Amino acid sequence: AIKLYPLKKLEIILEGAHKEFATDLLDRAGVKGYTIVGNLSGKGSHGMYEGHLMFNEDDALIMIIAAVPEELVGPLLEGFQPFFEAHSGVVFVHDIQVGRPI
Amino acid sequence: AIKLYPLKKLEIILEGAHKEFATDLLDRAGVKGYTIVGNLSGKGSHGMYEGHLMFNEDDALIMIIAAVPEELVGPLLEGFQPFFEAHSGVVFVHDIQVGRPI
Amino acid sequence: AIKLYPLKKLEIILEGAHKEFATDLLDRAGVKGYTIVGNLSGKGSHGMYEGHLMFNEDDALIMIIAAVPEELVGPLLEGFQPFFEAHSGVVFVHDIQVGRPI
C-alpha cells in the first residue's frame, strides 16, 4: 500500500572543512536529516556561473544529500550563496520520489 | 547511433550490516545488477513518514544503486517496507536515461 | 536573487584503472569540470543492452559526475561507446538544476 511523495533532492558538494557550516545551515532551515558521502575529489567548474571558484586536485570533497520539500529549496540556495562567493562548491537540485505506506 | 532508454534509478541508503539482505531482495525481484557506494554517514529523517527510524552518527551507511524498469519499482518498495518498519533507511526514486547503440 | 539553470547530470561508473581515459574524454569535449566518487563496487548489468560487459565483485569502481549542457550529452555518449564495447560500465543521464545569482 505504497504512495509516492515528490521531494527535491539536493547534492551539496564542497570541501570537508566546511561540513559543520553546511550542516548547521540545513538544521537552522528545518531540514529533517541528511546523509554524507565522503572521499570525493574534483576538478574545475561544476555547472556554476563563470568565475565561480573551481575545485582542484588537492580538495578533499564531500557530498551532502538532503531530501527536501520544494518550498525549502529557494531559501537554502540563498543561504549557501554567500558561502559560494568565497568557496568552491555546487548544489545539484533533482526531482525524486519517496514511497510511504498508506 | 545512440538512442536513450528511460529507466528508474533507485538510491537505497541503509546500514552496511544489511547489505546482503537488500541485495538478495534485488536479486529475487529480478534486478539485473547494482552498484554500491560505501562510507556514508547520516543523521535524522531523510524524507520518510514521521516516526520512521532516523539515522544517527554511529551508523555506517551504504548506498545501493539499481537502475530498473518502471514496472519493477512498486514491487521493490513493497519488498523493502517490512524492513524499513524496523530499520533506518530510505529509497530515492529518480528518472534517468541510459544510452544504447541502435 | 537566484535563478535556476537546467543542465544534464552524468553519472559515469567504470573501473578506476580507466579514470584518466574518461577524464581526458570529458576535457577534450569541453566539459568544464567533474567530481569523482571513489570506492564503489558492483555486480551485474546496470541498465545497458543485453550482452554489455557486467561488473563483478573484484572491480574497484569509481563514479565520475559531470554537469553538462544538454547539447554535450549526445557527443559524450558517442565518445564513450567504443570504450563500453570492451569494458564494463554505464552512464546515467539525469535532469538537474543549478542555482545562479541574477
Image (cartoon, coloured by chain):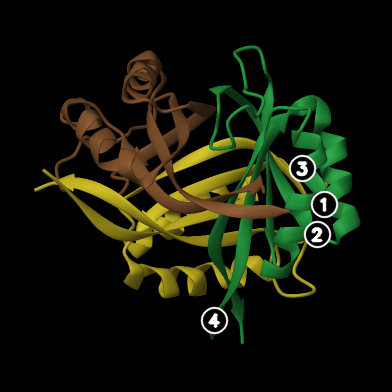
Chain colours: A yellow, B brown, C green
Determine which quarter of the picture holds residue C88: top right
Q: Residue at x 71, y 47 (%)?
A: C35
Q: Residue at x 32, y 25 (%)?
A: B29
Disc 4 to disc 2, how far (Cα)? 24 Å
Q: Residue at x 50, y 26 (%)?
A: B33
Disc 4 to disc 1, how far (Cα)? 28 Å
Q: Of C38 and A87, which appears nearest the observer? A: C38
- Residue at which label 1 appears: C26
Q: Earlier in the sequence, mark 1 or mark 2?
A: 1
Instruction: Answer whether labels 1 and 2 touch (C-beta < 8 Å).
Output: yes
Q: Earlier in the sequence, mark 3 or mark 1?
A: 1
> Vertically, is C71 above or below B38?
below
Where disc 4 sits, the SS reads strand
Q: Earlier in the sequence, mark 4 or mark 2?
A: 4
Please say whether residue B57 is visible from this viewpoint: yes
- Residue at which label 4 appears: C2
Q: Nearer the viewer, mark 2 or mark 3?
A: 3
Give the position of the N terminus of chain A as an image quadrant.
top left
* Neighbour tally class for label 3: few under 14, some 14-19, many 20 plus, Cα within 10 Å: some
